[PDB]
Amino acid sequence: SGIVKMVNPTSKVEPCVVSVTYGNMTLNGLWLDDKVYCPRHVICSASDMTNPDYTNLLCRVTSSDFTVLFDRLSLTVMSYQMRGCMLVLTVTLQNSRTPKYTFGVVKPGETFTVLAAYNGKPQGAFHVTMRSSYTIKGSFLCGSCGSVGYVIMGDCVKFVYMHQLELSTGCHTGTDFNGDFYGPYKDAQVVQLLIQDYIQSVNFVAWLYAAILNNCNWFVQSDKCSVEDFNVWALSNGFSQVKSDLVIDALASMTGVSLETLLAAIKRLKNGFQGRQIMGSCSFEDELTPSDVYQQLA
Ligand SMILES: *c1cc(-c2ncccn2)nc2c(C3CCC(F)(F)CC3)cnn12
Image (cartoon, rainbow, N blue to C red; front, top):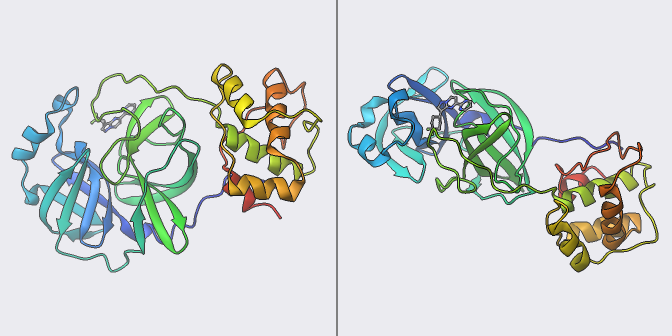
């Protein structure tokens, strides 16, 4: 028993973390095969950050201007390409430790592991949940840009995130591996307003199912609320739209408690828990998906 935010093992991703330097700027990159992916703002100086003209900045850049390090091993950049807000450098050396990998794009509510890196050196890992605002609540200092988020799917590493910006205190965003930012955010040093965030309802439902299997069911009552009725209520109560899933169905079968029973429970919990905790919390713990809790339940 017990429910915690678990990170995926890091062994497959650690040998891909590199340092990328251009001018006075050093950030992190991801070395897969003979390609090095990194944020494109590595090529802009402090004077060119409010509204950088990246295409004009790329004219003054040569492959020799990049210093790519895998610890002390210097990689030779043959060529480079700008793909959205990301640079894809081609190096002479294939990473012999490149794992089986794919690129993916996470949706709000989905979780992944961030391998925090500084100066191309992994420091540790942490669990993040993509918010409805297309931001994550991570821990990143200047120099952690280029740290990657990933999820292990089977024996494959699915890379989903490359850290780029801090939109406000403890509020971070980055791009997918197509170079597209999550949300409408841009790599510009300007104040950027956040997309509307919501309590990830299906993640809180997962928390409630996990609580039932962790000797906590006081919130379960005879009232039921359909998905349709919950989704209308959710619009005006800061909760995201709910959709049933095969994992929710498995959780309903393991506990004998229907989704509708928990949707009615959420509406009651919205006006207060009355000092009672659900697994040590009086908050809408929406950081773990149904799949995350399912892996910690029996
Ligand atoms: C380092 C630190 C930061 C930062 N730290 C805290 C709050 C906000 N920002 N930002 C940056 C950048 C930044 C430059 C502008 C940009 F290109 F648009 C995005 C990245 C670079 N290095 N740091």
